[PDB]
Image (cartoon, coloured by chain):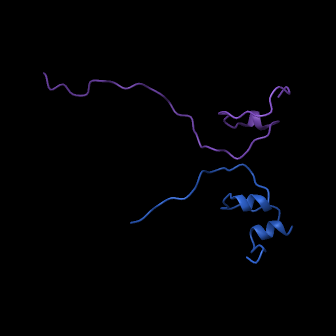
Chain colours: A purple, B blue
Amino acid sequence: LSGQADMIVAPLTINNERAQYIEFSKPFKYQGLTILVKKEIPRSTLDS
Amino acid sequence: VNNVWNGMIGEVVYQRAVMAVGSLTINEERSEVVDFSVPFVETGISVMVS
């Protein structure tokens, strides 16, 4: 915004607070927030 | 058709109407003749056979 850049080509998810005074193009992807978690190893034993 | 527009987009492009709320789809030529707004539902082309 402060005249220090002219192109911003990187993941820049569109939001109201940004597009209030900024220009955007038609999106080149379609994302959505999800939740992340790690899995677990043991599912069966066959040794009990 | 014949370099002229058959309604809908024609109605917007002939100043008869002011918006075209409905089930329009964005495209290169359509956005070339009339301005658009931010898309509000994702869609494309899909395959569906019984």
Q: Tell how many labels.
A: 0
Up-down relation of residue A34 to residue B14 (above or below): above
Which residue lies most toward the top here? A48
Where is residue B39? Give x, y as percent: 68, 50
Q: Nearer the viewer, residue A25 or A47?
A: A25
Picture quarter with the C terminus of chain B: bottom left
Is B10 positioned to the left or the right of A12 in the image?
right
Residue in the picture at 79% in, 62% down: B33
Q: Quadrant of the N terminus of chain B?
A: bottom right
Q: Residue at x 82, y 29 (%)?
A: A1
Q: Determine which quarter of the picture holds residue B10.
A: bottom right
Could you say where residue A19 lies in the image, as x and y percent from the top left? 77, 37
Give the image quarter of residue B3.
bottom right
State which quadrant residue A33 falls in: top right
Q: In this orientation, which residue lies closer to the viewer: B22 or B30?
A: B30
Residue closest to the eye, B43 or A8: A8
